[PDB]
Each structure stands twice: as structure tokens, then as C-alpha cells.
Amino acid sequence: HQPLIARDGPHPVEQPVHNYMTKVIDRRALNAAFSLATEAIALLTGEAL
Amino acid sequence: NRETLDELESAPQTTRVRADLVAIGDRLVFLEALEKRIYAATNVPYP
Image 1 (cartoon, each protein chain N blue to C red):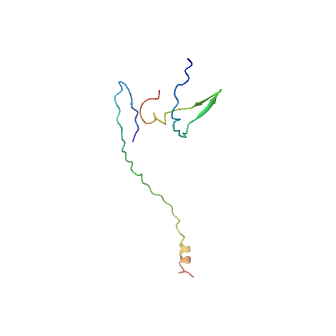
Image 2: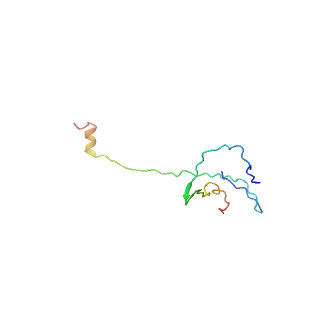
Image 3: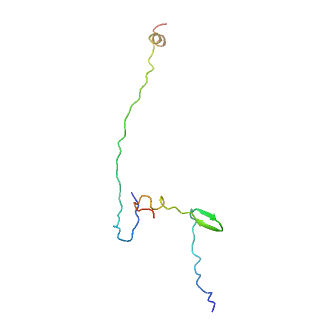
């Protein structure tokens, strides 16, 4: 909402103005991969002991 | 005939206001730049 100043003279009389706007959230997604080693499975899962 | 009466009445109520006072020479004066204060969003130019 915006303030106004009251003018005196041949200035056209100003009346309040209001502003409604609406921005849309930008979207994104991120990545990474820690992929495991074959033998390392057969160790930590037991399965090879 | 040396008219000294004049007028002094209410010693008016006072408030503490944030201002900017600078001493230039022997005088104390207010530094006012009123744009953000009043002219800011109003579209009226700053005189």
C-alpha cells in the first residue's frame, strides 16, 4: 500500500493506490550418488563370511 | 513606552524525537533530508 501527499493547486487530486502481486515458487531438485562396490555388499550383508 | 509584555503562556508539552543536529559555526541546526521520510513512494518530486 502506498502513501500519498496532498497537493495544492492545478495538480490532479491523487487517491491511494494498492498493489497486489503474486510470485510463483520456482522449483528444482538436486542429485548425488554414493554407489556401493560388489564385494563390499557380500561383506556388510554377511552372506560372505 | 517600552512594551515588554508580549505573550508567554503554556510552556508547551514536549517530546523526544530522533533528529540530526550539527553545529556549524556558533549555531546548532537540523540536517533534514526528507525523501525516504515523506516523498518516498508518493510519486511527488522532491523540491
